[PDB]
Amino acid sequence: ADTVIFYDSDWNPTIDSQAMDRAHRLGQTKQVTVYRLITRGTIEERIRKRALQKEEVQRVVITGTGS
DNA sequence: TGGAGAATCCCGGTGCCGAGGCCGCTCAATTGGTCGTAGCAAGCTCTAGCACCGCTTAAACGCACGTACGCGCTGTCCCCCGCGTTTTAACCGCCAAGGGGATTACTCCCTA
Image 1 (cartoon, chains in turn yellow, blue):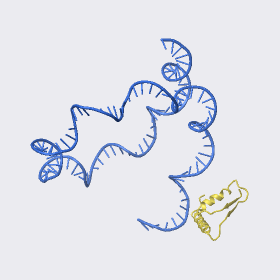
Image 2 (spheres, rainbow, N blue to C red):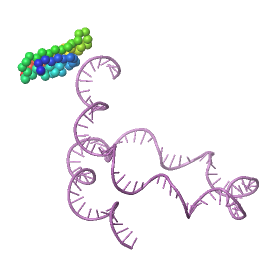
Image 3 (cartoon, chains in turn blue, green):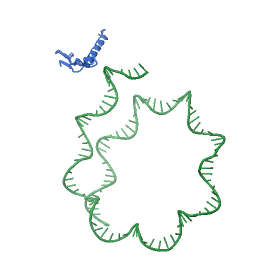
């Protein structure tokens, strides 16, 4: 595959970040695009904004290297 | 009585599969101590169970006597058995479905 479409965002960004990795792995060679069908003016928006701010916390809690 | 044949026995061979025995764990039986009680022992009451007597009558019982009903005996038949043919569907195998339930995920708000 080369395209991932989320019909739905999840409350946990790690699960969608895992889901979209399925196409974006050491075997991939085409460009990958991810689309996300956020229906505007709905709680689909708040679900995505909450999931997106969690990803910042999860990036802050890995500010220091694990290398 | 005899006999033929069909039905049941018995003896040996084969297999399979379940019973009897082994092993891990656990959890539920046992050891030891505390505390409440419950039912066991004494003592009192007096309840109603037992025994006896005398009268009444109505229930029991011995016997007369019949006739109503039990049972053996005869006839009939019809309908259920026994056995051969036809047919069906019960049993087995294998796959399918899904349906239920327990675990896991994640928000929201009660309640401590």
